[PDB]
Structure formats: structure tokens, C-alpha cells
């Protein structure tokens, strides 16, 4: 698609992140209103998830069961809520500072960009102790994405680059993006295509696996875009933070 679509969210303020499931539901962290909203597929009914105590929430990730994880950035914590429930669980991460992005794989491992500590932490599925990934030289990391092989990609926001670690590796790679400026979010698909909200340039870019020439996606009029999500059909959603809206492009 080369015509962007503005989704029928209403009342967003400075939205910070987006997640989608395979049922077409879209969740957004409506950061300026301390809330997480869900847009139901088809009906376009918007509902507010019954999280409690959020402040300036940033990242969001969802699993297929409809469990939602949010980085409660202003409270230095990560919380999750199962679908329709009124139980929220604080994950036993420790010592977070202004955390932003969050990612969750099919196994239920959770990764968080611990932005204010220049590190990426994880709670492996089945463990109650966090580990710190062996990235080096991060500055204010802003987003994280993971694939089914356990590769992890991070927007190293303060260094204008995207870094990746394969599972078991202690040495990161820098992806061949060009001219990024304070990138804010990242998403990956099962083919290895990587999408990045190039925040400081008001654009979204992608790299096919093996490509050395990023593609600027045909969004228009973005302002400080903040989060990106992609489903298995290659549709791309982006929180156009500065314009209080969510836009999408189908493949």
C-alpha cells in the first residue's frame, strides 16, 4: 500500500507505543493520558484497559492470549494484565530507570529497554531473576524487538543506530541503517525484516534481511513517531506521537 490509513482512535495525547495481535486488535500506550487503549477489530470500539497506577506509560507488547505488558515508565516498573482481568502483576525487574520499550516472545520471555540505565534486561520464561544482555555502549536505548530465533534488536537511540545480538552471542552487530536520528522504536518479522521509527527524521525505515539500503516507508506528515508494530502479513502500524494518531500501511 502507498496510501496511509489513520486509525479511528480518539482522544490520544502524545501516544508512545503500539502493539497488534493476529486478530487485528491494536493497543496503544496513550502516554499523555496515563492509559492503555485497545481498538477492537471491525467494530472499531475503543476501550481503556483497567491498569491502575500508571504514570507516563511508554512501551507496550501483547501476546496471543491477549495479555498486555506495559512499561510504566514514570514508576520505573513493568506491569502486565491478562485479558479481561482485574489483576495486574508487577514483574520482578530490579532497579529500572525510565524504562521504555518492552518485547515478549512466544515462550513468554520479556525484554525491557532500561533506558535510564543504558542497558537491556530480560526475565527468561520461568525465571524470577533478571539478566542484563551483553550489549555494549548503549545510550538511552528506546525500543526492543525479538524474533522466534531469540535474536534481539535494540534502537540505541542516543547513538543513532540499531544493534542486534544473536542468541548465545556476546558481541553485537550494528545494522546498516543510514542517517538515523534518535530512533525510537523497532519491530521485526519472521523473515528478518527490521522496521525502525526514525524519530528525529519524522520517518519510518526498514531493512530487508541482507539489504544494505533501507527503504523509507510511504507515511506522510509524521511528527516524532514513537512506536512501530508489524503483523505477519507485513502490515505496519506507527504511533505518530506528535500528531496524536496511529497510522498504518498494508504491504
Image (cartoon, rainbow, N blue to C red):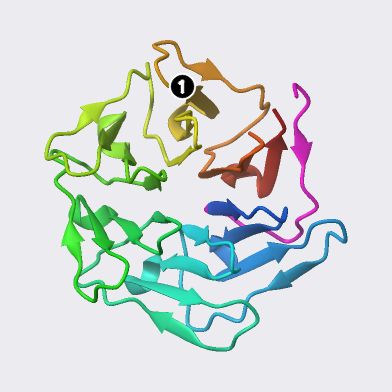
Among the 4 quarters of the image, the one containing residue 30: bottom right
Task: Measuring from the top left, give residue 140's x and y in whole percent.
Answer: 27, 46
The image shows residue 174, relative to residue 89, as above or below, that is: above
Q: Main secondary structure of the magenta part?
A: loop
Check the image and name the residue furthest to the top. Answer: 213
Position of the C terminus by quadrant: top right
Q: Residues within 10 Å of mark 1 (few under 14, many from 20)?
A: many
Task: Measuring from the top left, give residue 168's x and y in whole percent.
Answer: 17, 44
At x 37%, y 16%, the residue is 178
Is residue 67 covered in magenta? Answer: no
Is residue 6 covered in magenta? Answer: yes
**Horizontal relation, residue 56 to residue 95: left or right:** right
**Horizontal relation, residue 244 to residue 14: left or right:** right
Disc 1 is placed on an element classified as: strand
Highlighted magenta segment, given as a residue range: 1-16
Q: How many marks?
A: 1
At x 25%, y 64%, the residue is 97
At x 51%, y 25%, the residue is 205
Check the image and name the residue furthest to the bottom. Answer: 86
- Please name whichever residue, 40 or 77, is drawn nearer the observer in this view of the structure: 40
Among the 4 quarters of the image, the one containing residue 64: bottom right
- Please name whichever residue, 222 or 144, is drawn nearer the observer in this view of the structure: 144
- Judging by the rendered image, the residue that carries numbered circle 1 is 207
Position of the N terminus by quadrant: top right
Task: Measuring from the top left, give residue 117's x and y in whole percent.
Answer: 19, 56
Amino acid at each position: 500500500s502507498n496510501t496511509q490509513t489513520v486509525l479511528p482512535f480518539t482522544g490520544l495525547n502524545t501516544p508512545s507505543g503500539v502493539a497488534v495481535d493476529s486478530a487485528g486488535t491494536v493497543w496503544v500506550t496513550d502516554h499523555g493520558n496515563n492509559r492503555v487503549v485497545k481498538l477492537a477489530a471491525g467494530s472499531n470500539t475503543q476501550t481503556v484497559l483497567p491498569f491502575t497506577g500508571l504514570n507516563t506509560p511508554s512501551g507496550v507488547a501483547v501476546d496471543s492470549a491477549g495479555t498486555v505488558w506495559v512499561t510504566d515508565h514514570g514508576n520505573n516498573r513493568v506491569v502486565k494484565l491478562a485479558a479481561g482481568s482485574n489483576t495486574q502483576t508487577v514483574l520482578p525487574f530490579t532497579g529500572l530507570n525510565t524504562p521504555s520499550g518492552v518485547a515478549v516472545d512466544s515462550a513468554g520471555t520479556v525484554w525491557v529497554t532500561d533506558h535510564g540505565n543504558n542497558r537491556v534486561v530480560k526475565l527468561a520464561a520461568g525465571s524470577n531473576t533478571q539478566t542484563v544482555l551483553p550489549f555494549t555502549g548503549l545510550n538511552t536505548p528506546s525500543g526492543v524487538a525479538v524474533d522466534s530465533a531469540g535474536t534481539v534488536w535494540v534502537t540505541d537511540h542516543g547513538n543513532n543506530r540499531v544493534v542486534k545480538l544473536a542468541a548465545g552471542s556476546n558481541t553485537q552487530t550494528v545494522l546498516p541503517f543510514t542517517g538515523l536520528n534518535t530512533p525510537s522504536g523497532v519491530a521485526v518479522d519472521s523473515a528478518g525484516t527490521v522496521w525502525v521509527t526514525d524519530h528525529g527524521n519524522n520517518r519510518v525505515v526498514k531493512l530487508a534481511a541482507g539489504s544494505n539500503t533501507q527503504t523509507v516507508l510511504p507515511f506522510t506528515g509524521l511528527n516524532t513517531p514513537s512506536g512501530v508494530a508489524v503483523d505477519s502479513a507485513g502490515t505496519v502500524w506507527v504511533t505518530d506521537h506528535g500528531n496524536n494518531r496511529v497510522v498504518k500501511l498494508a504491504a
